[PDB]
Image: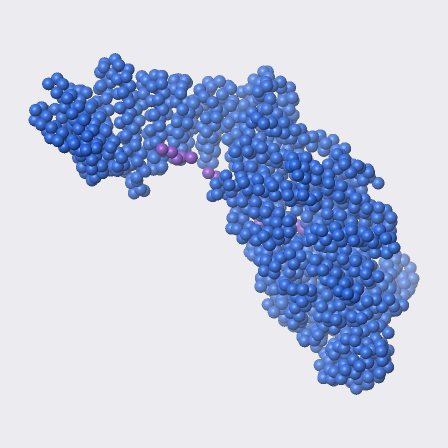
Amino acid sequence: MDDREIMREGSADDDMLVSTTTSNLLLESEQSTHLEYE
Amino acid sequence: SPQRALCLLELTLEHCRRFCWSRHHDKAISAVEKAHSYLRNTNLAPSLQLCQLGVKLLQVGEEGPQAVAKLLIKASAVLSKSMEAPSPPLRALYESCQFFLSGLERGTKRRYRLDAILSLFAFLGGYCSLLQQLRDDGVYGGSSKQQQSFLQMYFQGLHLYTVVVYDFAQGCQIVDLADLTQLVDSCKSTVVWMLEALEGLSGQELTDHMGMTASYTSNLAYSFYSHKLYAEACAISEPLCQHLGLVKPGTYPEVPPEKLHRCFRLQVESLKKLGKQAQGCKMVILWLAALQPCSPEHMAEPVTFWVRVKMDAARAGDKELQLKTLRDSLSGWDPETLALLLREELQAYKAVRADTGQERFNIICDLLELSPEETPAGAWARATHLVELAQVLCYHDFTQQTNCSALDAIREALQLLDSVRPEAQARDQLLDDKAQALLWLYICTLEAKMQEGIERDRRAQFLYSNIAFNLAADAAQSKCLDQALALWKELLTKGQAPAVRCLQQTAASLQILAALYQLVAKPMQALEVLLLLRIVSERLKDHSKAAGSSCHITQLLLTLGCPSYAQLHLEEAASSLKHLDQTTDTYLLLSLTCDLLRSQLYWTHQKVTKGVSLLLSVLRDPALQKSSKAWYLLRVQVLQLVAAYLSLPSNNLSHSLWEQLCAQGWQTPEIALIDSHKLLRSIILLLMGSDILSTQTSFLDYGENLVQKWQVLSEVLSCSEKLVCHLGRLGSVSEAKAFCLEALKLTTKLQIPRQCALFLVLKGELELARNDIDLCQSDLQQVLFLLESCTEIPNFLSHSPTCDCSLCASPVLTAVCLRWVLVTAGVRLAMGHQAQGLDLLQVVLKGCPEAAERLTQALQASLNHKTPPSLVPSLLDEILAQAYTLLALEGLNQPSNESLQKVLQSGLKFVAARIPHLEPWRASLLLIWALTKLGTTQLFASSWGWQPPGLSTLDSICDSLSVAFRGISHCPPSGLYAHLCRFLALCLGHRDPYATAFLVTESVSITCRHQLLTHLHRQLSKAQKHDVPLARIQRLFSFRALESGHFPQPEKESFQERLALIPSGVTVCVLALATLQPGTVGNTLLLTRLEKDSPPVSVQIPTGQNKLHLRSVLNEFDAIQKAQKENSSCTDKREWWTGRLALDHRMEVLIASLEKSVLGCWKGLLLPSSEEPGPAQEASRLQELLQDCGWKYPDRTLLKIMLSGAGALTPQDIQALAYGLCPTQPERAQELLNEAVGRLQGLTVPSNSHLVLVLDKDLQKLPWESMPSLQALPVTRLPSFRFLLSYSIIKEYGASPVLSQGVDPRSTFYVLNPHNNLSSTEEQFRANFSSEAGWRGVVGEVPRPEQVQEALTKHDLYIYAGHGAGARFLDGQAVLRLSCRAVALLFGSSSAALAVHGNLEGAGIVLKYIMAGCPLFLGNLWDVTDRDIDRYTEALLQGWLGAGPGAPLLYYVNQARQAPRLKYLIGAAPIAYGLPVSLR
Ligand SMILES: [Zn+2]
């Protein structure tokens, strides 16, 4: 003769990889620049 | 006399000639003294005497500089005296010539001091004055030969000065300071005199004189430039170039362009470096003016200089100099010449590796104002300049300044180009121009589509977008690339060299086109483009580009599956490397790429040892870590090759090489694959920005980035495909789904339908693995729509074997079609439609070889090789192998088809031909073969001591399974590994107890092992960027940490090593279900009891015979769960409670059935073993007597364990044990056992003993802990026994404070009523919780993720009393990245439940908590109601927190099960994961 109890819900799952931190790779260095004759 | 002086001079000349050989000029020196006596005063005579002293010195050749200096000083004094006096006799000139000849002989010494140089300068100045006086005389002008000879001698003199100054400069160290610093003044003087002399000379004489003078001035400037006194080097070089340029155009017609190029080059270089740019640019203008009447190829270098000075001026902050162009300075030049110069400035600006948007925009604007539109040539030139404008506006926002979009500019350019009627000569240039316009139309339309996608994502922050691909654009846009390729093929395939202005642009555009083809998943057309690039590079003699193109061809050919053609192109690439400078970064990069390609070829050709050596050398090379984007891409390819080598079984490589490879940082292929993806994403961030891959910079288009952008996009899609396939094959469907979704988002952003279809098919397979038929069918229907959209029961399976359609000509589309058929067959077989599934599988079986043949023919047609590829390319072999595996399993279901039986042998032959590349499928087929040979008591009964109350077939089955096990054990798929291990454990039995125990242990929680290995790699990388326990745990969980040997010796040694680390007092029981049909649930239970200092005990319980079998128990559990879900819908309270009470009674009967009808007498294998000596003596006595009764495998440990629980062994259990172990004389055994139990009555069960339960993904569902025998024992669950060892390792280093010290009851965080749904729960726990000392939490509000993270990392106890497990507040991935210190009491529905989807292993957040290091995890196995779980929570909290310090949590977990009204529906729900935990 008791009332009804509410059933707790077990929700659930995205599992997104994210991890966008990255190592901020070093940009290509300058890497910039014949005059030999008698 | 009038001719006496001439006679004396002639005699002295003959004397000097003799002195050159015989030194006869000594008697002639005496004769000269006699002449000076006869002629008292004669300047010619004194000069002759000085020249005689110099001739003596030249006979000495080289001597002290003092003598030469004195002789030259005397000569200078004599010359000054003669010239000052009015005596310009030719005899003085003859004496000076003799002295100069003597010095030239002395010039062979090539040794002169600064003083010697100055003295020679003074002598040369006197001689020059005399020569000028002689030229002033009318005699020189009267005879042209006389003037010519006078000039010849004059320039010969300064030429000697040149040689002297030039040699003096070389023979000088850094110490030489003022030496050249002063020599430079006289250098300016000589230049001035030489230029002054050039006046008057005309014709060939003039051309020669400017030539020579320029030659020596260049020689002196070269040396002066080297001295770093640029200021001095300029001062000398100014007037010559000023004269050479400001003259009227055409005055100097034949002076060589390069000879002028040198002098101007030196000045501009000096002008540039000295830091003043302005007159450097003006010098470039003067340089162009000097060469104005000539071809443009010479003007190319002056143009490059202009850009260098201007780029440096822009860098140095100057903006006024940045603005000025050549139009603002070269006014007056014929527009044609001006336009060609502007084209060269644009090209030099493109060469720059910086940001040059406005600079190019300004040039394009001036070019467009300059070209007259009305003329046809003007329209064609305007079209070209509009293509340039299209590029600039395609990657920069100048639309407000120009009032035109890139698309409109390029479309107008195309309209202008299609109206061009060209001359027969300029047809090739039109071809190249149209190809560039079409390529850049494609690029700009693609960029606009990308920006639309980015804005679309930024607005609505996607299966609708997948079908939202406009077909019109797909065909029309792709046609642009096909037409550009046709034009370039026409231009380049001809024998004659193309008659185009810039073949360098053609090569760059071809690289961009090849990158685009590889992105649009059209690789054969990329192969054609790369063959054209090699033709262009060979014409340009650019060995770097030829080598790079050959390397790309080899890579693409290996990806397509052809090793022999790749080998041909690899040797072609190797040959070009020899023509390259070895100190250049390009050479190193291409050599390392070639070594990587040889390593891959050796891998494909089964030369694994050589390939491993090469790969190791590449990995250990210090140059690989250079910070450049090409080096990053090389590292990506290196990582993919590492993954390829890690997928090989252990027998292919020796132990030492395996350790050497794994020591580089990656142990499993997926780890290496994930790192390649991360590196690719970092490259994408460097090239562009995060917008292409995320939702929220400037792109530097210096040509290199252009091709690299598309290359990296193609490579990230390829790496994602590899990762998805590998992870799905393993069984990690969630991570594979995540990668697939990311890739699909990228492909929808870029609007590529082929790659979209590929990833949709992969997603469909992943959803099929989860038994989600609805979403799988949705994905497959999307695939079908995309395939019908790209092609212009499906129609592509009706195509002819030799078909030339879009689907059949493209290997990618053919693979997608076959994969779609495979997934559709799987769906039909999972829906119970056997026939249609089998027919679809047969379609796949037929299709794969036909597709291989078509690709073979297409490859031969593209590459024009006479011999066909040795073997058909191997890219569809995995699809064929999977089809064979599925058909063999289906034949297992139907043992009476007689064709599917032959399919097993066909598949085994196919896979055995391709060892070791198809090993997982070989293992699956071998397992199916073993099952066929197996198909009651079954053959396992002879190998097991307890039967329930080579040559032999079993030996052959064991050998086959051993081969399969060693084929997959290095990187095992979860389901196949579990099946193989448990089948081998059944076969081995008690013949090898240790091998059986190892096999049972290895079969549980393999996916968790893979995930832990990946997480450990991430943590080690994080630590290294910013570890001994981590290394030990990685070695513990590794798959390759085995010695060499035959099965199962190294595995047994590793197991015994693991057995030695078991903590004392811990009993490990592994319960596993033996499955004799993949996809089903077995009725055989494998139980292994692992203890310290005790041999492992294993028992098989066949439950299929009993009416209550394991499958029945699982079905009843699922029925109870379903009814519980259905009962909550009821609104009548009384009926609701009646249903709840019935469900509780069903649960109680289920638990009783577990203990009584699944385990039976063996329940004692789960119970602790006594330390009292009675049971051991009893077992020792009983072993012999029972061996006489018929015990096949007498085990003292088993008897001791069973006899240690003699106080509760019922006569039914004793009868079962006796009648099972001893089947020949059962009653004698029963009598002995009964007597032993009688003498063992009154034993004390050990107190400090703990049980760890390792269950199967199916057996984990059941409430084992609530069995009547286990209600008084401390029981927890662990994913695996290696997790117990990892817990011990962590505990040694003090990384688990709760397991080392205890739980501080004041360090607690609670989340109560987070969603404000459960009001009864809050009122009951709010005050009690808030009133506790040091307790902090969130009531009525959603906790922030930082709050939950601090709860888990900083507190010792975490209590969640809301809905579910709170996976929304902190998802499993966040929990993984933390260190779990707290005890997680998650009171919610299905909190500790693992979701079993299909044949995949259970998944849940409890696993993430355990891998994060949680000491203990308490949660519910199924769904509960709020009030009764509140009663359980209150009882547990009161009992544990009120017990006092040093109170075990598990004791009050067990005691609190009596609190709920529903004892077996609510009280049986809570289970504990981890290790026992007490209070501080
Ligand atoms: Zn076709």
Regarding residue B456, the answer to whether it shows in the image is no
Is residue B1425 toward the left or the right of residue B535 in the image?
right
The tint of chain B in the picture is blue
- How many numbered marks appear? 0
Residue B1017, above or below B1289 = above
Left or right for B551, reference B323 = right
Tell me, yes or no, if residue B309 can be seen here: yes
* Colour scheme of the picture: by chain
> In the picture provided, is B493 more to the left or to the right than B1220?
left
The image shows residue B364 at horizontal and vertical percentages of: 55, 26
Going 62% across and 47% down the picture, which residue do you hit? Answer: B601
Q: Residue furthest bottom?
A: B1239
- The colour assigned to chain A within the rendered structure: purple
> Where does residue B23 sit, x and y in percent of width and height?
18, 33
Q: Nearer the viewer, residue A15 or B802?
A: B802
| Ligand 1 placement by image quarter | top right
Q: Residue at x 61, y 59 (%)?
A: B654
x and y percentages locating residue B461 in the rendered image: 71, 43
- Residue B893 percent location from the top left of the image: 85, 56
Quadrant where the image shows the C terminus of chain B: bottom right
Tell me: residue B1314, above or below residue B943: above
Residue B1076 or residue B174, whichever sits in front: B1076
Q: Quadrant of residue B861?
A: top right
> Which residue does the image show at 56% across and 37% down from the upper left?
B546
Image quadrant assignment for residue A3: bottom right
User: Which quadrant does the N terminus of chain B fall into?
Assistant: top left
Q: Choose between B3 and B894: the one closer to the eye.
A: B3
Q: Nearer the viewer, residue B258 or B34?
A: B34
- List the single residue furthest toward the front: B22
Q: Is residue B1425 left or right of residue B1285?
A: right
Tell me the residue at 84%/40% (across/down): B793
